[PDB]
Image: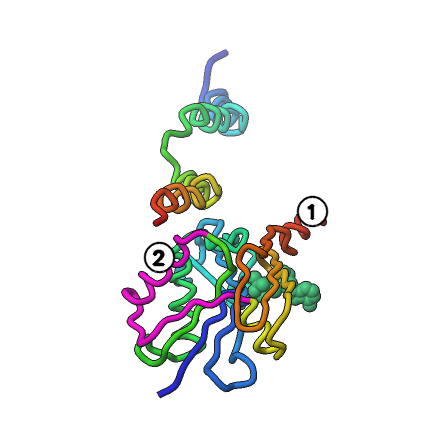
């Protein structure tokens, strides 16, 4: 005969019960703007790299000093 | 006072006073550094590691090898090694002794000049000498003439020595030492 408390509470409840809507709204929306940094993890990477390769390590001494021998 | 000798024949590194039968202890001349973010905040970060300490610690450390082909690659690293060796093993101060240096023969002057420059300046040390392997090899083996083959960690040698003299033209010098062989092994 009506639209009621009973039905309004039904709608309210259903809203509360729907996990898909609210969880998707929070998680999927927040998922997209996720990331911006010059990561320190990559600072580690870079530093290690610096330590990594003979072309820096040996050559820095050997090209520089064996220039002048005598 | 008393007199002290470093062996820098490559591989583990050998140091000891005159007249002891054998050096006090010996170290690879590995050098190594961290590879990973340091994530125990409780840990003290030390950024470079050497010697059996490293030999234990190795896994996250990664190695640099400061002597190629008997030629010592990176001076300041050597200086780290050297300082460590004196203080940690030797409990010795640079003033304390003459010090004797051990050299691949027939190799670039630079090792001579910087080695001496550093060790007289950075260390301050009563007396210095650098000596060619074969001479020692004879003295220990006690035959005044000879020819020596010694293929160490580093560059591999032929020297005939006659009694009391050098034949520097005679001499052959080769980068064939066991390290490169080992890398062939893989
Ligand atoms: N038990 C062993 N058997 C065979 N070779 C070894 C053994 N221990 C060490 N070596 C090798 O001997 C060398 C040790 O360095 P060393 O001979 O002192 O070189 P250097 O002549 O430059 O001083 C390295 O090549 C090392 O791999």
Q: Nearer the viewer, mark 2 or mark 1?
A: 2
The kind of secondary structure element at disc 2 is helix
Q: Residues within 10 Å of mark 2 (few under 14, many from 20)?
A: few
Q: Residue furthest right?
A: B185
- Front-most of B50 and A36? B50
> Mark 1 highlights which residue?
B184
**Quick check: marks 2 and 1 in contact, CB under 8 Å?**
no
The kind of secondary structure element at disc 1 is helix
Of labels 2 and 1, earlier in sequence is 2
Q: Is residue B41 visible?
A: no
> What span is colored magenta in the figure?
B108-133
Residue A49 x, y percent position in the rendering: 45, 41
Q: Residues within 10 Å of mark 1 (few under 14, many from 20)?
A: few
Q: Is mark 2 within 8 Å of ligand 1?
A: no
Q: How many labels, in total?
A: 2
Which mark, residue B114? 2
Residue at image coords 31%, 69%: B123
The answer for how far apart the CA atoms under marks 2 and 1 are is: 32 Å
Q: Is residue B87 magenta?
A: no
Read off the chain for label 2: B
Quadrant of the picture in which ligand 1 is shown? bottom right
Residue at image coords 64%, 51%: B176
- Front-most of B136 and B88? B136
Image quadrant assignment for residue A36: top left
């Amino acid at each position: 005969x009506x639209x009621x408390x009973x039905x309004x509470x039904x709608x309210x409840x259903x809203x509360x019960x729907x996990x898909x809507x609210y969880x998707x709204x929070x998680x999927x929306x927040x998922x997209x703007x996720x990331x911006x940094x010059x990561x320190x993890x990559x600072x580690x990477x870079x530093x290690x790299x610096x330590x990594x390769x003979x072309x820096x390590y040996x050559x820095x001494x050997x090209x520089x000093x064996x220039x002048x021998x005598x | 006072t008393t007199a002290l000798v470093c062996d820098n024949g490559s591989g583990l590194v050998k140091a000891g006073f005159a007249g002891d039968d054998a050096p006090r202890a010996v170290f690879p001349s590995i050098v190594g550094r961290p590879r990973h973010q340091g994530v125990m905040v409780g840990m003290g970060q030390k950024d470079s590691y050497v010697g059996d300490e490293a030999q234990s610690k190795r896994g996250i450390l990664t190695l640099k090898y400061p002597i190629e082909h008997g030629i010592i690659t990176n001076w300041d690293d050597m200086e780290k090694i050297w300082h460590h060796t004196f203080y940690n093993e030797l409990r010795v101060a640079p003033e304390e002794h003459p010090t004797l240096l051990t050299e691949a023969p027939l190799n670039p002057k630079a090792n001579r000049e910087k080695m001496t420059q550093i060790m007289f300046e950075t260390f301050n040390v009563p007396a210095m000498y650098v000596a060619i392997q074969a001479v020692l090899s004879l003295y220990a083996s006690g035959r005044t003439t000879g020819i020596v083959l010694d293929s160490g960690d580093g560059v591999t040698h032929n020297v005939p020595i006659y009694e009391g003299y050098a034949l520097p033209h005679a001499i052959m010098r080769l980068d064939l030492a066991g390290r490169d062989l080992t890398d062939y092994l893989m």
